[PDB]
Length: 174
Ligand SMILES: CC(=O)SCCNC(=O)CCNC(=O)[C@H](O)C(C)(C)COP(=O)(O)OP(=O)(O)OC[C@H]1O[C@@H](n2cnc3c(N)ncnc32)[C@H](O)[C@@H]1OP(=O)(O)O
Image (tube, rainbow, N blue to C red; front, side, top):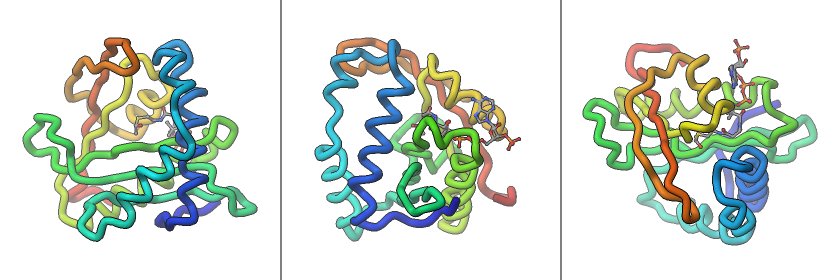
């Protein structure tokens, strides 16, 4: 239903959306061991430390169900040294619980963050997504993202490919 900035009380819910969607989306792509390892508590604490840090440049958003549960979230911030001059912002994470997907929540989250990054003066934003994640890829391609590059990372013990999509913030109306 609605999108808003996250508060500290929203984090336990943010952590569940994160872990549950990671588990549902990366089955057979990211090692089972690693996926089983994710922690609701660990995740909630990590975001909590960030939210509590006054100088943290990250921006957090959550998507609410009709009754108010946190069923989606998105984090935006400065790029994390991706090596693409001209791309100063990055979509750190965006996840919507499987059953709440394809109802416009991801788009709404995306637009809210891009709007804020635009107001903060970032010219362009990129996003990294697993080469083997059709869901996220299809979503970004549909939204206009242009393929920028790729890199191999290692999650769990697995070496995996990741691709980047670029989006224009300046000038565009989000
Ligand atoms: C940010 C990094 O972590 S990359 C990882 C991204 N997260 C994941 O892959 C986790 C699994 N997936 C999800 O959480 C969600 O599906 C997301 C975040 C990828 C997308 O959010 P959703 O709410 O499902 O998409 P939403 O309903 O807002 O779709 C918006 C538009 O994109 C289109 N779209 C969304 N996904 C796809 C897709 N996979 N293929 C083609 N089109 C798509 C929708 O049809 C819609 O089109 P429309 O505006 O013309 O009607």
